[PDB]
Length: 437
RNA sequence: GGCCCGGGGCGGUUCGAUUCCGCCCUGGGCCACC
Image 1 (cartoon, rainbow, N blue to C red):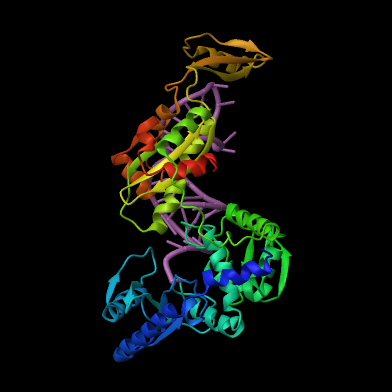
Image 2: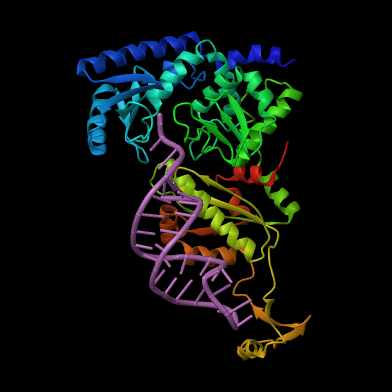
C-alpha cells in the first residue's frame, strides 16, 4: 500500500471496461449515421470525444452547430426537433439552455444546440465555449486520459465530483485542466494540499498566483472562472482529502464510501444523548429541475437558520433532503425551550427625551436601570424552536425561494421526535450530527 | 431559478433604522442545466 501501487489497482476502478468502450463506440457510430441522414452540422465533445469519461459514467455529447444569427428560440425549436428524431427515447428537462437527453443503442446521449462562433469571447448561449474547450483540450490531454480518470473517480467517490448546484464541486472540464496543468493525478493531489481560498490557477500563463477567491482561469476565456461553482467548503474537503491520501494512501479513497444503514432506533438514542432540539420543515417538492430546487432549498434552510440564531435558539447546523415527493429542511438546536421574558436595551439615563418614550410603552414588568442605561423586560410570542419556525415559515414563506416558498405557503408541517425518524432523513441527520461508526 | 453590485418606492418592529425583519418596481453582472 504505497501510493504508487494503490494507483495501479485504482485504474481498475476508473478505466472503462472494454465492453463498455465498444458499447459507446457502437452507439457513437449509429448516432453519426442518424444525424448524417438529416445532414445537420454537429460535433462530438466532452468526456467521450476525449476518452476521459469515468468508468461507468458513459454519456455521449453531440453538439449541433448553428449560425450566430439564429434566434435562441430557433435553437430551442430546431435543436429539440433534431434530437428527438435521433434518439430511441428522450427526456426534455433543463433550467435555461435547451437540449434533449436520451438513449441510443443503450448509451446515454446529450444532444445540445449551440452557436458556432469564432473565438469564445462573448458567448451568446450558455454552452458556446464547450467546442473551443474541446479543441484546446484534445491536443494537450492526449496520453493523459487515465490520469484524468483517477482524479474523476477520486472526487466522485468522495461526493464532490459534479459542478452543478447539487454538488458544487469540480467540473469534468476543471479536472482536465488540472491534469494538463499539474501533469498527473498524483502531482495534482501533491500540490492541492497547498491550495488556499485565494489560490488562482492560470493554465494559460502556466502559473499559480494569489488572488481574491479560488479562481481557475479558462485557457479559452480569461474572464471565466472554471471553478466558479466550487463551494468554499468543498475546496476545503478536497484539499484535506489530498493531505490524508498522501499520508494514508489507501484505495478506499476511490471506493464509493459506506452505504450507511444505521438503525432509526440508534439515532433517537443519540439525539436523547445530545439533548438537543431536532426537527424538520416538510413541504411538497416543486415540480422543477434540480438546478433550480437546490439553490432554493439552500436559501430556505439558511433564512430559517438565521432566524433561529437571532432568536436565541442557538442553532447548531442545518441540512436539506429532497425525496421524489417532499423536501425536508433539517435543524438541530441547543435551546429546546427558552423563557417568556427577555431584556430589551433602552437609552442611557442621560438623554430623557428617549428615556421617557421608552418607559411610556405599556410593559408588563416595569423597566430597570443597569450600568447607566434603562432595560426592559419583554415577553416572547413563542418559547420553542418549532413554535418559532412555525410562525416564521407561515409568515415569511415568500423569501424562502420562489418555488420552495410558494409550496410552503400552501403547506408545511414541523415533524419532531419519533415521527421524524420514520421519514427519509435519517441519513442526512447522521451526517449533520457527525455520528460515526 | 440562485448569488453578487447599484436606483427608486414602501410596510413592520425599535427610545432610536439607510443601518433589524420584510414587500413592490427596476438597471447591470455571474452561476447551475452542456
